Structures are given as C-alpha cells and as structure tokens.
Amino acid sequence: EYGAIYSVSGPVVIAENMIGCAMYELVKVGHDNLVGEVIRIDGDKATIQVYEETAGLTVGDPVLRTGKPLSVELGPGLMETIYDGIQRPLKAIKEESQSIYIPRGIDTPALDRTIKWQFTPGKFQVGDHISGGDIYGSVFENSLISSHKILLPPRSRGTITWIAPAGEYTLDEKILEVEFDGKKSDFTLYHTWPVRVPRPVTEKLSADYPLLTGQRVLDALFPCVQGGTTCIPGAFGCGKTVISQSLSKYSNSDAIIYVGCGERGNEMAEVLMEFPELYTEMSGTKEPIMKRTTLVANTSNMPVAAREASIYTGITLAEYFRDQGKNVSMIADSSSRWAEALREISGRLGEMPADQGFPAYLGAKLASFYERAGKAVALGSPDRTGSVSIVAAVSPAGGDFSDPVTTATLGITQVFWGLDKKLAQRKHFPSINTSVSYSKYTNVLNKFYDSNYPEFPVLRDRMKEILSNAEELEQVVQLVGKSALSDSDKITLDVATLIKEDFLQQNGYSTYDAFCPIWKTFDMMRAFISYHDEAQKAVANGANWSKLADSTGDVKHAVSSSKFFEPSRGEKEVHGEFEKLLSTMQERFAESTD
Amino acid sequence: AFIILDEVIKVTNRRVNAIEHVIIPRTENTIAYINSELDELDREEFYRLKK
Amino acid sequence: FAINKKAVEQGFNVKPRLNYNTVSGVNGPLVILEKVKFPRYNEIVNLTLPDGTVRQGQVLEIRGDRAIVQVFEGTSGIDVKKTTVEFTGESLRIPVSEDMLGRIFDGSGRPIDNGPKVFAEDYLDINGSPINPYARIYPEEMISTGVSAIDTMNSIARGQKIPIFSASGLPHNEIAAQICRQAGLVRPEENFSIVFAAMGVNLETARFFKQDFEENGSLERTSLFLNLANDPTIERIITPRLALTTAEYLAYQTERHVLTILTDMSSYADALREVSAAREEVPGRRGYPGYMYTDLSTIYERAGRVEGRNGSITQIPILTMPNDDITHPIPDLTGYITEGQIFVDRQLHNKGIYPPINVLPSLSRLMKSAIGEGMTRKDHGDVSNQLYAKYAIGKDAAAMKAVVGEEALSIEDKLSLEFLEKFEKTFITQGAYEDRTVFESLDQAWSLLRIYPKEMLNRISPKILDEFYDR
C-alpha cells in the first residue's frame, strides 16, 4: 500500500506503486517523513515535490499518503502563536529540540494537544437538524477574547445524536456525533481546511463602515473603509513600522494577522522582539497585543513552497476568524517577495516565461487573492456578521514601478498611501506625500458622514484645494517672490504652512497626539477652515493683513495649541471647549475688524 | 550691461526649457523601446532552446 | 555530558565498502554506472583509473538501478573496461576540531600547510539546518574594522551582512586582506576569530595572502580555505559551505565572536551556472539558473546573533559587477538579501585614493543599533550625518565652480570646496598598514569639521557642538 522511490533529482522525486492518489495529495516521503505533494501522475509513477533538502535519500524508501491537499488546522489556541509559512509552531519546536535549528523531518501538532479547554454547550439538543457553519458552543480563550465560537465545518449536515455537556476537554475528545447516511461523523474542538479553496459564505456585502486608524491625515483625507483593500510602498527609510504599529494598537478591529512573507531575517527578529512589548489600554492596560494576534514568520532560508503559501495561509486564517462574526485585518509585508517565490517555483518547474520573465498566473492569482477579501454575513444559523481588510505592502525591484507586480497591485487595490523618504529627514513623521496618495472610498463614506458628520466631506475637500493652491502658489513665489502676491495669496500660503505643521505632522509619542479619535479631528479641521475663511473674508472688505496678523497672532497660537489639547478627557467636554474656542476666534475677528 | 544680461538670460532660460521639455522624454521613450526589444529576443531564444 | 555514549554508539561500528567495475558509458564531465545496488543521492565515490590514479566524484541522479557520477578532476583517461568505482555510503562530511586556527585548508578541506592531519573532534554535514527565526535577536554592539571610511561612516554591528561591491580591476583583495588583518572588537582578545575563504583566485593572489598572513601574525586567528582558479568547479561551490559550517560550529559551540569573509561571489555564480548544464535545466535570466535565489539565501542567511548562546557571527561577501552595472542579477539579489552595501569607485582609484571608496552610494541599515554610549562615543551618529551632507554639498560645489567661476560662489561654497579636497586627501586616504581606532578617526573628523564656523554646523546637536568643538 506504500510507495517505493524510483528516481531522485534535486528537489524532484518519482514514486512507484502509487495508484489512487489525487493530483495534490500530500506524501510523507523518506524514512524521516519529509513532506511533499504530488504534481504529475503518469500511470503508476507520480512526480513529487519536496520541501526540505533531499540529500542522502536512497531508492526503495517507503512513501505514504496523507489524504488531503495542503491544509491548515483551525481551532482554539491560534492567538499568541508564531507560525511558519506552512502552519508550523516555532516556539514548541525550539523547546522540543532544545537546538537553534529546524531539524529536517520534524512533525508536531499545529495546535497544542495537551492544554485543557473549558467548553460550554451552545443552543442545540439531540435530535435537532443541523447544517454546516452553525455555532454549537463557545470556549473562553483569553480575557481579551472570551467568545471563541465553535463551528460545524462546511460540507457537513445531518442530525446530532450525542453532544458532550459542559466541562473541560482537550483537542482529542469527540464532543459531537452527527448522524447521516453513515453515522461515522465525529467532531472535536478543531478541524482543517484546504488553503487554496476560499471558504464558503452566505453572501458578500458592500463595505461602507470606515476603518479608523487613529492617525489624523489617514482618516482625514485618505480613508479606508472597513472591509476593503489598500496598498503602501515598501521602502527602507520610509519607516512603515509606525503605520503597522498604530494600526495594531489603535484600530477598531478585533483580530490582527501579521504575515512576514520573506524578509532579511534580522527584521523578523526585530519585529518579533518588539510586538510582545506593545501594550493596549482599553478598560485597563490589557498588557499584550499577542493576545490579539497570530504572526506568520518566513525568513529567506525557509523552503520555497512554504515561503510562497504564506499569504494563502494568512488569508485563510483571517477568513476563519471573520466567519465567527468578528472583524479582522490582514497585513502582508512584501508581496514582491511572494511574487519572487512564485516565479522561482515556476522556473524550477521549467515553464514558459512571460512579461519580464514572470509566469502568466500573476494577474489571475492576485485578482482572486484580493477578491477573497471583503465583507459578508457568515454562513450559519445565528446570522452573525464579520469583515476582512487586507493591507498589502509592495516593494519595488530597485525603486522603479514598471514591474508587473506593482502595476497589477495598483490596478487591483483602491487606496494608496504614498510614503516619501525626503520627509523623514525633515521629520514629517507621518511621511505621506499628499500629492500622490489617494483614496476611492469617499463616495460610500459620505453615506456615513451625513449620518454622523455631515460637513466632513466639504471640509476635507476644502483643505485638498487649499493645499493644491498653496503648493502651486509657491512655484511662482520662487519666480517673482512674495512681493508681487496679494494678501489673499499670502494668507493661503501661511495657512497652508500652519496646516502642514499642525494638522499633518504628528509626534505619535506624546500622551495627547498618540491617538487622535474622529470627533477631535472633526473639530480640528472645522476650526482651521473657519479661521482661514474668516480671515480672508475680513481682508476682503478691506484691511491690511499684516495688522490683522499682528492682532490675531494670539488666535493663531491658540488654534495651533488646540492640537496639543489632551483627548480622552470628556469626549464631549472637548467639544464644548472647541465650541468656546471657535466663538472666541469669531468674536476676536469681529472686534479686530473694528 | 542690462541689455547683455537680459538677452543672455533669455537665451539660457529658453534653452533650458527646450532641453527639459523635448530631449529627456525623447530619449527615455527610446530607452523603454530598447529595453522591450532586448527583453523580446530572450523569449524566443528560450523557446528555441526548450524545443 | 552523555555525548560520549552517542559518540561510541555510532563510533565503533565498521562497515564494509562495495566496489564496482560496471562503467557503462560517459558524457563529458559525467560518468554512468549501470548495476548499482540501493544507490544514495549525493554520495561520495572514489574512482580508480586503469593507470592506478585516483579521483573523486559525487552522484547527481538515480534512475531504477543507475547512478550518474561527475568527476572533480575532469574525466580524461578513464575507460569502460578497467576502471573500478568504490562507493562511500554517506554524504560529504567535514572534520571539525577546535584547533583549525592557524592551519590552511584546500578547497575540499585537505590541509596544505605541510602539517599533520586534522585529528577531528567531530564530523558534521556541510549544509546544516536553517536557524529557527524565533530564536534570533538583533545586532547590538559594533565591530572595529580599522578602516577610516568604513568604521566612521559604515560601522558594522555584529550579526550584520554587508557586501562590498567592486569592479573587475580594483584592489578589493588588498582591502579584504587589510580588513582581516586589522579586525577586532572595541574596548571603551580571547573572543575573536576569523574565517577567510577564497574561491577562484589567481596563484599570485593566493601566494600573497599566505605570505602576508604568515609574517603578520594574524594566521593563528584565522583558518583559510584557498581554492585556485584551475581547480574543479564543484570544489568551488563546496568551499563556502565548508567555511560557513566551521565558522558556525565555532561561534555556536564555543561562544566566539567570529567574522567570515568570502572575497568573491561572481566566480561562485559561474561555478553554479556550470552545474545544471551537466543536468538539462534550461538557462534562466542572463543564462544564470533561475533558482539561484534559494541557494544564495542558504549561503547568506546562516548569520546573526542567537538567543541563548553568547556567540555571534558576521559576513562580508565581496561581489564583482561584470560591467559596473547594478542591474545585473547577482548584485540585485545580494542587495535584496543583505543589508546595505559598500561601493568602490573607479575614478577615485584612478586618482590614487586608497582605499578608493565613495561614500555617497554607501549605506549601512543597522548603524542605528551599532553606535551609542558605552558601545562607543556619543557623537558618532551626528558627525556621520554632518560629514555625509557636507561631502554631498562639496561635490556639486566643485561641479558649479567651473561654470560660474569662484567669486560668485557663496562663502559656504568656498568652504565646502576646500573641505572636499581636504577630506579626500587626508581622511579617506589611509596607508596600507595604517591602523586607526574609532576614537582617532572621530578626532580626525572633528579636525576636518573645524573648518566651518561653529554656528553653521546645523545638523549637529548644540550639546555635542558645545562639548567637543573646543580646541
């Protein structure tokens, strides 16, 4: 029933006596049980792909069959875990081996098989008809998340003849007996799923609810809807780590799945050392972020197939967590590396190249992968709802954006947050080049603004035109100097500078400017536009703007200092203070005109 | 001196504008075309070797 | 301590060795046995030609009862009637002992210092398993190269991987020799060691390396793996694996801060293209194999500090761009895998500047973790930026000098013009045997900075300006 090796060639192996094997089964080739997958079947012999190094193999070694394609186990215990590209626990492996290597031919359960979990029955009873995707019990996973639900895997129906009652169990105790034509069906606290097949869902919806990150510029001018895609350039000096950290700590999501898809290694060490120290404070300083995140690490040494399947694994995990009714936020690291791995695999298979040497799959693969994102209502009885929002990170070949990867990604995604290094030295620490970055979810977000903040769109637009006008104005200012410019032009210029240095720039470490909520930013841009338009109106009827600036230097300083105002104090008393400041500015301008 | 400076600056400014607005686009389009052709050749060479 | 039980268990067990005479065809650098029994991929074999000469090889493929051996030292003189092929029964292994230091090894690891055998303390598989990422940490402290233009502006934190790009006809080898000779830690040594593996080099360069390392005493801190140009290519691809394996053993089983150098990778790329042509894998981009990314990653990414052990490791691969273009695949991949790069300009070399390094394109991403207090003085990070900015300004100032005279230039422009020449002629220009500590280089940089008025050095913090600008 086993298979004897018949040939070997680097990473290529040919089995024998293989009858009754699918085209993508998994096989435990070798005495050490190296993992592999069948590719081509020709009668009895079948080509096999290996992951580890094949040195030392010998003809006649038995070959086994797993019985499924590449799959990932899902269940309680994912949180606080650090995984390889192919669902391999690294902490447990290191502890078990006591070495500092990944000893080839090592197999340990993806999830711990010893920790006892306290299960609580759901809402069904014996003899009740059931359908796939229906919740039938919860589990307390952490103080942060305590409602880790238990589903019935899709493609499974029937009636339940026995359900275990409350108690404490491990992951190897059948807690349900679904009866069908064959009553063989048993179920435990976990199950598996092929990675390459998208999870079934009742129906997709239209994402409209905004995703707020806590930054000012992001949600002010280039918002991302909670459920959509986005892209940000990958550079060394840009310092994207700030964006990822802020998204992890201050966003309104409920589960983060960071994916390292091939890095220099040392960067992986840095991020792994850093994450367990980031702290969030909601209803008290809930110490870790690891209690809300699972991380997939893939250094360059990792096997090519593992380095390639990383994003598929991550997105599958995200979809699983979405179907529980929670909100998820995937974050890739370098899609360029994933494309590199895909091209390397294609080349090793010896297939026809395409544009710039890449294969022909890239377009379709990326399109499908991105389409896997979105917002939908889960598949089950309770009718919960979730959402997924991928955040890609494209790195170029050598800076140029002519590569197919960048073109396809930009064509697919909807939001781009351009980062510039030049701002780094000037320390606009949120280093967003406002002349390039853009968003396309405004048309939907207006249907939320009107319900909550009707004036937001006109204000954000107004500052968009203000910034464009100021940057254009400076061009001719250099040519002819400010001398030949009217007072209105100088007003535009200086208000643009004030906005640049207050509204956009953000320390990110001060207790007050670390995390700016929505209403606070609402008040800020309202106040800034009011100041500018009131000043220009006052100048319109006739007045030397120099004298006006001399009179209202205090008002300008007050509006600037309003940014230093500490939020998290009343969250409506702040609104009262902002109203007081606005009225004070109005009456000060009125008196100044006199 | 005023007349000479005026004419000199006019000439140099127009020359700079002409260079920027004509030469660089013309040469970089050719760069892209050459890159495309040299990428094309290897494709058929690889096909032949594969055959 | 129980390692003795394992050593004896697999130690005192002799096994026989087959011997074949069924050579049944040959194709260039290959050889095709016919009726092998239970072959084993990637074995080691010892051919015996009819004249009594002896060679070696390593299988590549196995059909049903067949092997395809490739011989290291060519294939001429073999025969299909009298040659006898002897199998080994286990892959290539290296003899490892603490006392490599001082000795010189050939490409395959046979000592060539006219000394006794290694007296191995153990045996190992050359290509070990990858490091577990979860058990890895960040660089922290600095390594003292002794070169002014490197340490001051491109410090190397232990655990980094900084390649040194260079052109064909440049003195990169001399720079590498000087670096290996002057390396060491910083004391604001009983823990330092170097591995210096050279692949694909002339005879003159090898002799110069040996003679210089002999009479300069550095030999007993190093262990060279020389491989001349006329030696088999397979041995070439093998050599870096041996060097990395021995360095890893030392670092992570004796807790020694070690530094490794390679002195070339283009010739490694050539040796690699040669393989997969013996096989029928069609050529990839620019003729190179497509899958070089994986194996180059394997070579490089056995570096960095480790969680538990106190040891460490560092790499300085040396490339050679064919026609001085970064677009070539080799430098592209190396930059992709490694952190920052060090350039070597041709023009500076033409002007007699040694080491002919240009700093404008240079970069080291882990600097920020290298400099600091205790680990070094407090003013390194500011002087670095200041000097970089002023050099960049001086270049363009010299450019404009020819077009707009000299008087129209601002006072800043004249000062920068003078500073550029002074910097080039004094700071970077370092004697072949002039060794400088980081402190001395910092002092010289301060001396050069003293050209400008105190106020104008904007990028430097006022605190440092007040503290050190005096005198």
Image (cartoon, rainbow, N blue to C red):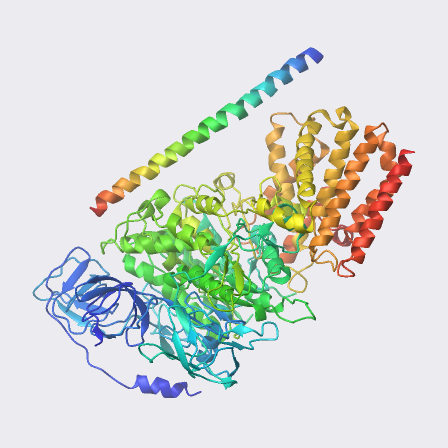
Q: Quadrant of residue A29?
A: bottom left
| Residue C155 visible somewhere in the drawing | yes
Whether residue C357 sits left or right of residue A585 in the image: it is left
Q: Residue drawn at (36%, 57%), measured in percent from left and top?
A: C199
In the figure, A359 relative to A153: above or below? above
Quadrant where the N terminus of chain C is found in the figure: bottom left
Q: Quadrant of residue C310?
A: bottom right
User: Residue reaching furthest left?
Assistant: C81
Q: How many marks?
A: 0
Image location (x, y in percent) of residue A528: 76, 43
Whether residue A344 sits left or right of residue A411 in the image: it is left
In the figure, A495 relative to A575: above or below? above
Q: Residue drawn at (21%, 77%), measured in percent from left and top?
A: A1
Whether residue C84 sits left or right of residue A230 in the image: it is left
Image location (x, y in percent) of residue A119: 52, 81
Residue closest to the eye, C272 or A392? A392
Residue closest to the eye, C366 or A470? A470
| Residue C421 visible somewhere in the drawing | no
Image location (x, y in percent) of residue C391: 62, 41
Residue closest to the eye, A201 or A20? A201
Image location (x, y in percent) of residue A426: 67, 45
Q: Quadrant of residue C169?
A: top left
